[PDB]
Each structure stands twice: as structure tokens, then as C-alpha cells.
Length: 22
Length: 48
Image 1: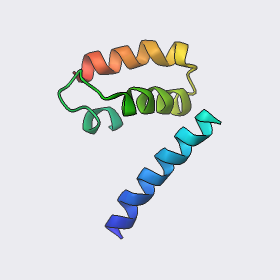
Image 2: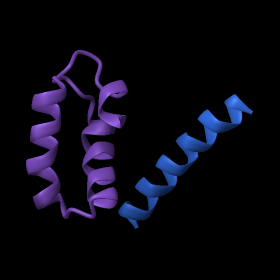
Image 3: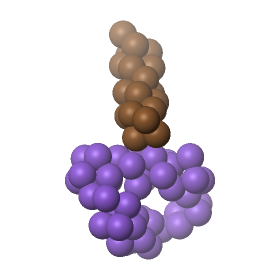
């Protein structure tokens, strides 16, 4: 679950950057 | 918090975050890159 927490933090950062590009 | 771990050698922050920071600033602080920039400068300068 700690690995889930680190991976989902990266997923939110990638989604935020994708929204800024769009 | 995001500026400190994404820092490498202090004031040398890779563009990957140069923007990621600018954008989180542009998002969390909702600061258009104009406003975000001044901040990016201060954070990098200070966090350096």
C-alpha cells in the first residue's frame, strides 16, 4: 500500500500536467 | 515539499519540475505562469 501511495502520487502529477497541456 | 525532493543540487532543478513546480504553483496557487514565475524564482533561490 505504500507502493500504491507513491505510484498514485505520480499518477496525479502526470494527470495534472496532462490537463495543463490540454 | 515538492521543491525540496525535486531539487538535485539546490538551485539546479530539471525542467521536468521547473514546469511541474511552475504548474503545481500554477495549479495549487492557481498562479498564471506570470505570478508562478516570481514564485518559482523565490522557491528555487531559497530552496537552493
